[PDB]
Amino acid sequence: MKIDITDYNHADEILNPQLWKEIEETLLKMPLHVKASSLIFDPVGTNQYIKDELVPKHWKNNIPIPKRFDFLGTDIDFGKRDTLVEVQFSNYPFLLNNTVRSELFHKGMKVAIIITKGHMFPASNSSLYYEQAQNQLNSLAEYNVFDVPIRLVGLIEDFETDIDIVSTTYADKSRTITKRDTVKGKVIDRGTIVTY
Amino acid sequence: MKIDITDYNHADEILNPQLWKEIEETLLKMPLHVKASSLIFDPVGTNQYIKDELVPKHWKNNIPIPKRFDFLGTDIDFGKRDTLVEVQFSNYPFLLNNTVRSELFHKGMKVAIIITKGHMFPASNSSLYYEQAQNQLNSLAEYNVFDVPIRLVGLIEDFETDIDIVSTTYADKSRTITKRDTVKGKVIDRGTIVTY
Image (cartoon, rainbow over the protein chains, first blue to last red):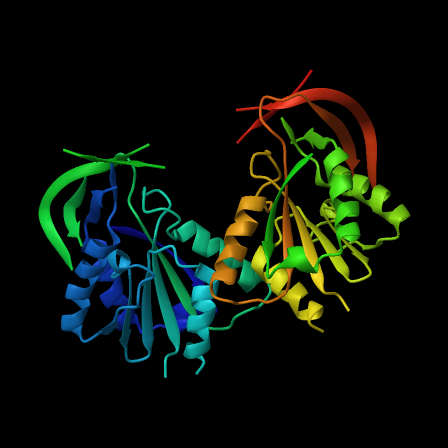
């Protein structure tokens, strides 16, 4: 996928280039994961993909307790050396969520990378999106509310362009994949995901 | 105008019925104030109307310093006895704005009334709206973040219904009214304000 980046409190000069590269390379070669709602962004598939890539690179992971069993895996955290990676795709309250995480951060870790998906992707209801997270952080930054270094990453794709897509069907009850296919497609014109 | 109300921390049992009545009666007989952007919600006209009604009823007022001269008057505060009324129509960061106001509130006032306008009204860019403020407060309430009693009020109008409208044109430079008319209209189908 493609990515848009917003750095706060000079996360760019603080971040270990190699640690950032591991995250960046993983995201760039990663296809768009989608599932039925028709086709919507699949955060669990996405986090599973990220996890399988970073675990072998020695990133320690932790999966936050979901407000709903079938939501488990919608958000995931990774840590390595002094870097914290927080994938936030759920509808958990953004500012409150991070204010709470910020507290622990200040009580070691020196920079945090937050991964979100662009608004262009149709998704679960009220689920966080990049532009919204950026707006909120731009606002706090404006009044010097926080000093923690943050690299905010937005997962996006260009419109009307052939891309690799992974379509999955889950039997959410224990979660199971009953069907999956790796096809080609693109996003039309929020956007609409089209498969070939 | 019509109003929708959401109470937090039992603002409803704490609020002086007469103090609430002064606020409620003012809002109910108040027409929809609009101006050119075509026609959009006019917060200054609205606050001027509210101010002219409450000052004679002994509500002390205070107008917050705007982040922009021509924005001055977009938000206004009123106090009387133990009640705080905060009209919030601007794009100032909601949670941060109120967290800061909350701090002073806890350092007397016993309940706060926050007035916003519904999402149905086309308005200034990124300006706060009722449904958004409610979502954010519902979220903080969910995790017992604040205990301050709040009555959140949303200014709305029914669709396809004849209503009184005040259309104004300002020479924003010192603010001046160069043109104004009191007509009839309605909101079609965000919504679109139509005048007759």
